[PDB]
Image: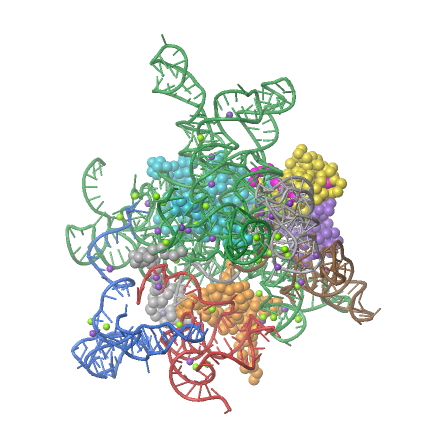
Chain colours: A yellow, B orange, D cyan, E purple, F green, H brown, I red, J blue
Amino acid sequence: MIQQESRLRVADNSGAREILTIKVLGGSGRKTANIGDVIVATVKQATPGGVVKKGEVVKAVIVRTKSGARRADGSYIKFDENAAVIIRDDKSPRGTRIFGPVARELRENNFMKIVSLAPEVL
Amino acid sequence: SYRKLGRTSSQRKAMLRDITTDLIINERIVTTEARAKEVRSTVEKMITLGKRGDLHARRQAATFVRNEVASVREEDESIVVESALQKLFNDLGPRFAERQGGYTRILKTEPRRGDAAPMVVIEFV
Amino acid sequence: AVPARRTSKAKKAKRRTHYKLTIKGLNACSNCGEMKKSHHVCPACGHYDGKDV
Amino acid sequence: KGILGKKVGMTQIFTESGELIPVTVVEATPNVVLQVKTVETDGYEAIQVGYQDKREVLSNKPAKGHVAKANTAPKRFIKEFKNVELGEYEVGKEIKVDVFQAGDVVDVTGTTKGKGFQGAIKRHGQSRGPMSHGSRYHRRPGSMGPVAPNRVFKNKRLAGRMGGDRVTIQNLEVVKVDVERNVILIKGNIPGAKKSLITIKSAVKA
Amino acid sequence: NPLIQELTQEQLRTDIPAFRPGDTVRVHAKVVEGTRERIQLFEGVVIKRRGAGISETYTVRKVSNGVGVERTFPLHTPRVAQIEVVRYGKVRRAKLYYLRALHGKAARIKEIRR
RNA sequence: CACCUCGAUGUCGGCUCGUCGCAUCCUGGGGCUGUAGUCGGUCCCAAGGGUUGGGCUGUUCGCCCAUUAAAGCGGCACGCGAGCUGGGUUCAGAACGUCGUGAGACAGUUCGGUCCCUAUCCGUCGCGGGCGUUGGAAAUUUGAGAGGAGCUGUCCUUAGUACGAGAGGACCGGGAUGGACUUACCGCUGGUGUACCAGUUGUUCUGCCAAGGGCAUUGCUGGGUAGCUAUGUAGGGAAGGGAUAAACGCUGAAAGCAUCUAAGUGUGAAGCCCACCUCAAGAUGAGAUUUCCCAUUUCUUUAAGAAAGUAAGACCCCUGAGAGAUGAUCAGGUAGAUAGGUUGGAAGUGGAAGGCUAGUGAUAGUUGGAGCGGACCAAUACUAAUCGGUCGAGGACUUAAC
RNA sequence: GUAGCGAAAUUCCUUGUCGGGUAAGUUCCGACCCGCACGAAAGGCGUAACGAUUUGGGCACUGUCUCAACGAGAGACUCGG
RNA sequence: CUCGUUAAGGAACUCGGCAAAAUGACCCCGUAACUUCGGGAGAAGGGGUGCUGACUUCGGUCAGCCGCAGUGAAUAGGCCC
RNA sequence: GUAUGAGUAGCGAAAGACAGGUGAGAAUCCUGUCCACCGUAUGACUAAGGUUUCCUGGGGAAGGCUCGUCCGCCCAGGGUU
RNA sequence: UAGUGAACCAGUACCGUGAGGGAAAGGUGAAAAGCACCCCGGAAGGGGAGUGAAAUAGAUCCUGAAACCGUGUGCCUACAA
Ligand SMILES: [K+]
Ligand SMILES: [K+]
Ligand SMILES: [K+]
Ligand SMILES: [K+]
Ligand SMILES: [K+]
Ligand SMILES: [K+]
Ligand SMILES: [K+]
Ligand SMILES: [K+]
Ligand SMILES: [K+]
Ligand SMILES: [K+]
Ligand SMILES: [K+]
Ligand SMILES: [K+]
Ligand SMILES: [K+]
Ligand SMILES: [K+]
Ligand SMILES: [K+]
Ligand SMILES: [K+]
Ligand SMILES: [K+]
Ligand SMILES: [K+]
Ligand SMILES: [K+]
Ligand SMILES: [K+]
Ligand SMILES: [K+]
Ligand SMILES: [K+]
Ligand SMILES: [K+]
Ligand SMILES: [K+]
Ligand SMILES: [K+]
Ligand SMILES: [K+]
Ligand SMILES: [Mg+2]
Ligand SMILES: [Mg+2]
Ligand SMILES: [Mg+2]
Ligand SMILES: [Mg+2]
Ligand SMILES: [Mg+2]
Ligand SMILES: [Mg+2]
Ligand SMILES: [Mg+2]
Ligand SMILES: [Mg+2]
Ligand SMILES: [Mg+2]
Ligand SMILES: [Mg+2]
Ligand SMILES: [Mg+2]
Ligand SMILES: [Mg+2]
Ligand SMILES: [Mg+2]
Ligand SMILES: [Mg+2]
Ligand SMILES: [Mg+2]
Ligand SMILES: [Mg+2]
Ligand SMILES: [Mg+2]
Ligand SMILES: [Mg+2]
Ligand SMILES: [Mg+2]
Ligand SMILES: [Mg+2]
Ligand SMILES: [Mg+2]
Ligand SMILES: [Mg+2]
Ligand SMILES: [Mg+2]
Ligand SMILES: [Mg+2]
Ligand SMILES: [Mg+2]
Ligand SMILES: [Mg+2]
Ligand SMILES: [Mg+2]
Ligand SMILES: [Mg+2]
Ligand SMILES: [Mg+2]
Ligand SMILES: [Mg+2]
Ligand SMILES: [Mg+2]
Ligand SMILES: [Mg+2]
Ligand SMILES: [Mg+2]
Ligand SMILES: [Mg+2]
Ligand SMILES: [Zn+2]
């Protein structure tokens, strides 16, 4: 459950390290975002030499959350942290490498490139 | 569920232990409606421990029953003092060895003058 | 808030309509025949369900 | 199609393909058609149905006489079903859970659990006032309206008794039917506490 | 409750091994990326067992790529081909929630070889 | 302007709660277009629903950030302070600029500065009692009327088709999945869970060891049943009728023509009446059906008379919860599983005590998934629902028919 | 009207302009100086230490909030006084 | 009203982080700009703490043991620009 | 003087339980047992102040925010070397 | 409720540190003949029996108004603004 002002780690190498949520896209009054949702965020801490830089407004997709996802088979998955990946408008990740595991929910959301780059999918 | 009897948790536990031990000692006491309807379960569970009779049940009961003098007799020119716990496991357990629960009865009596609190008599069958 | 207007005798009596006592559960005792509350020990003879207590 | 049952409780079931779905277990001892109402005798068409056999000591001579037509024991619950084919029913006829097949879409009616006296926040999902910043307005029902009417408009929702209302859930699914046990498994949850009366009917929307 | 037990007795599985929280288990979980079906092995310590009957569930925790992950499975789900008890650990409580805060060496569990 | 209020009508903004108007912000229908298509512009009909989260500022407003289908405009004492706040206006303190010879003051700023009231009446939200509904009762019911709900995105397909030189790119139709809202419920994920389990500190008590109790926020700490719960789960605003708004007609004269209208006849909107959900015969117009009881006794007066036993039935009283402020509702009262206990389980906790074994010891292993186990489940009349009492009909008249 | 300071507890115009901070800053910080209407003992400027002083930012922290849920006690509620 | 707990988020609340939360004892390491050279300073930021043996220069050290957690409860600064 | 509000607000920080006794009458007085509270005090002395409130035996009109068989209250005796 | 504040143990009770301020409160019956005795009750208070011309003159005592409270019932009242 990611909402405005919520801070997430960046699970790629685009340059941003920690981002802050500005909006939860997809609804007028939408409050919370979970895995596979796209958010507008700000880079509150960036790698010194990265492409994306501090204070830049960017879109990202939540790739794992502390409150995770419920699968149709009755199972659940939960991660130890909230991490997102900065993406272009076409869902292609801004960075080139993904760090840490990623949830399988991104496949049906059609983040195929992110899923392929992920070192592990659960 | 259980009644709060208008007390905090610790105070309610202390009052229940007192009244349960009093009923063990006397075998007949007068209290209010709610107090009797709670003391019945507690005292019957104590008697269940007494029926079991083993050391483990004795210690469990000791956690609850107070350390009072159930009675005193004079035997062999010696004063023998029997505690509430000793009376339980020596007299009440053997007494009810046959009954399957329902060791106590509650008789409704007239309301108390000071409060009109419904009074009852609780005793062993 | 305070009573804007005093309450008249008629309205006062109307409100107290339901402010009355009741007596219920009285019936003859088996042992002595005096009136007793049902499910209670007959205070006079101290008998209940045909036995002294 | 309709039947009366008892809300046994809630559990879950694995369907084909291994999906896990929550189900409500509703038991329906075969109901008995106690009376048939027609346009001629009553002005409308419906069938009265009884359920949950009742001990004789708990019934009245009028109640026993009423069920005497159906030639069965006294019933605890009696309800009328409309929008059915009177030709297919007659006094004394039985209705069993096998009326519904798995995958049928039904409407389930019950009596919501009673919450007793409840404040506006819980009862109507209203917003609280701030809990700090000097606020002395936490769980109150808001303003009562404008000055001009010199009154409070009706439907100004306030605290009061909550629950215990007749509620219908539409378009539930009959996950399974066990005729031997007189049980219907309905996907989801339905109003009412365990052992309460439940009314299953074929979904009107369909 | 007895009626519910009878209804769900059929779907209760039987090949469930004897494991308790604190033991390392490998779960052969079935997944579908479409028509094709595949088995993914989720190996980790059992952090939690709760519920009863058909409703019983268990949670398995593993640290993958420096991020902790927990998967909760129904105990009688057919989507899990097999549960395999890799090791028996020694724990003193039913719920190992404290493991979430621990990292690496701190989170190690002593084996017992039941 | 000075008509009510100065023996007091609290004054901005915000919060809680909304309600209403349409001069309509989105969604719906349509005309015109300098409407190719996608977009639009303007106008007409339309108030059913919806119409945001932040940075700054006491702010309204406004600017900005990011979204949205849209981020409407207004009334209700610039709605709402016996509902809240008190940041500002504005008391007394103090200071700056300024004015004054001065006390002081604003043609201005800045820091700090007591928000009282137990609801009588109406009104509003819930719940009972009385009587009525024309013999007395137990159930099931129709619906006069009333309330609730009413929103909408994106994607796929039709189809890169129609249109277009290309760029670009549909109408109509058919699917999938969301946002917000909302009705329920605890099987799942979690929360809580002060008479559940365990660890542990200090001190004190049970004479001591061992084992426990008391107090320390429930001493603290880790879990957690029932119940109550959302962020959890399931469902809903689906389809379709009838009369219409603007608009478009068909036929058709007045007026040989023309003409949607005068007669006649039709299409047509998230709107109106239904449809869906809920309440509902105190609907004094008190409705309807099924079933039960039976025409008793005494005295007055022909009385729709009076009282007194009852019948069907209900209640008092008592055991209770799925109910509950109290009433009430519902489950029961030995024709008994209503509660308590007992017995057996379950959740839950996590390996009791007493032994044994190893170790110098802390402690570990074993006896043994043990012990304990509020509300959960199933049996069991062992305990208590005993014994009893109160109330409760005999059914008017007139006129059709039979 | 010198030095010094200056949109200041003083700047109405004013949210002055520029720079910093923020995704966005009428507040805040640095600078500029057309000082409406600073200025040298009704002291000017600066200043370590100090402040239940006023002001802005950051970490930590959280039911302050999204958005409320449960539990304990007292009153409320029923009965007697 | 007083009090305990709270999923995910963590000031988005609000005039204002008001209130609450958080820090808190001792021991060791370490500690900035600036400064009136005293301070700033308990800056900051870290580590240790229970129990049982062995040895000690008596403060430690080593070895082992247990728990989620050792100033295991109560009492004790939030910090920085 | 008596109403209304109204048999309503309130009954002034916290633990009591049972057995026995007394008595016309007992949750409230006495005895007993356990429990609980304070313990740099809620303990022991004292100055001021109060001025008989001290003790014994009676009483339950009024006072005691309930009750009271009881009292720092009322009645009668006595008490400060 | 007049008449001195004070017809009565009044400059008192009471209020205030003090100066000072400052009340309320008359009536049995001719005569106490002030209800022996009995009954209910622990008492209080009643019912008899007595005193008295009168006790609804019984010490809250001449008369005994109204507000206010209550009992009994001749009439009306649960579709009414
Ligand atoms: K005025
Ligand atoms: K409005
Ligand atoms: K148009
Ligand atoms: K509208
Ligand atoms: K703001
Ligand atoms: K106010
Ligand atoms: K007002
Ligand atoms: K009024
Ligand atoms: K201890
Ligand atoms: K103690
Ligand atoms: K009726
Ligand atoms: K300047
Ligand atoms: K100036
Ligand atoms: K300062
Ligand atoms: K200060
Ligand atoms: K809280
Ligand atoms: K918020
Ligand atoms: K502000
Ligand atoms: K510092
Ligand atoms: K440690
Ligand atoms: K400190
Ligand atoms: K008065
Ligand atoms: K009154
Ligand atoms: K005495
Ligand atoms: K007289
Ligand atoms: K009268
Ligand atoms: Mg305690
Ligand atoms: Mg809100
Ligand atoms: Mg009006
Ligand atoms: Mg004039
Ligand atoms: Mg006035
Ligand atoms: Mg219009
Ligand atoms: Mg900020
Ligand atoms: Mg206003
Ligand atoms: Mg007002
Ligand atoms: Mg001057
Ligand atoms: Mg201050
Ligand atoms: Mg649940
Ligand atoms: Mg459950
Ligand atoms: Mg010991
Ligand atoms: Mg103590
Ligand atoms: Mg500026
Ligand atoms: Mg000056
Ligand atoms: Mg000078
Ligand atoms: Mg100076
Ligand atoms: Mg939280
Ligand atoms: Mg803010
Ligand atoms: Mg805001
Ligand atoms: Mg604070
Ligand atoms: Mg500590
Ligand atoms: Mg009142
Ligand atoms: Mg008191
Ligand atoms: Mg102290
Ligand atoms: Mg004395
Ligand atoms: Mg005395
Ligand atoms: Mg008294
Ligand atoms: Mg007279
Ligand atoms: Mg007189
Ligand atoms: Mg009418
Ligand atoms: Mg009438
Ligand atoms: Zn008797």
Examine the rendered structure and indicate whether residue F37 appears above or below residue J13: above
Q: Nearer the viewer, residue F117 or H74?
A: F117
Residue I70 falls in image quadrant: bottom left
Query: Which quarter of the figure is the N terminus of chain C placed in?
Result: bottom left
- The answer to whether residue E112 is left or right of residue D44 is right
What residue appears at the point 68 percent right and 37 percent down from the top-left corner? Answer: A87
**Rendered location of residue F88, percent (x, y):** 53, 49
Q: Quadrant of ligand 30?
A: top left
Q: Is residue F184 left or right of residue H23?
A: left
In magenta, the rendered stretch is: A13-29
State the image quarter where residue J58 is shown.
Answer: bottom left
Q: Position of residue F277 (x, y in %)?
A: 45, 40
Q: Nearer the viewer, residue D71 or F184?
A: F184
Is residue A53 something one can see in this rendering?
yes
Residue F223 lies left or right of residue A116; in this view the side is: left
Residue drawn at (39%, 71%) of the image: C46
The front one of F85 and F249 is F85
Numbered disc total: 0
Q: Residue at x 36, y 55 (%)?
A: C4
Q: In the displayed structure, would residue C14 be above or below residue F207?
A: above
Residue at the (34%, 64%) spot, across then down: C27
Q: Say whether residue A24 is magenta.
A: yes
State yes or no: residue D81 in magenta.
Answer: no
Q: Is residue I36 above or below residue E84?
A: below
Work out whether residue E80 can be spotted: no
Q: Is residue F212 depicted above or below D169 in this figure?
A: below
For the C terminus of chain C, the quadrant is bottom left
Q: Position of residue F76 (x, y in %)?
A: 42, 43
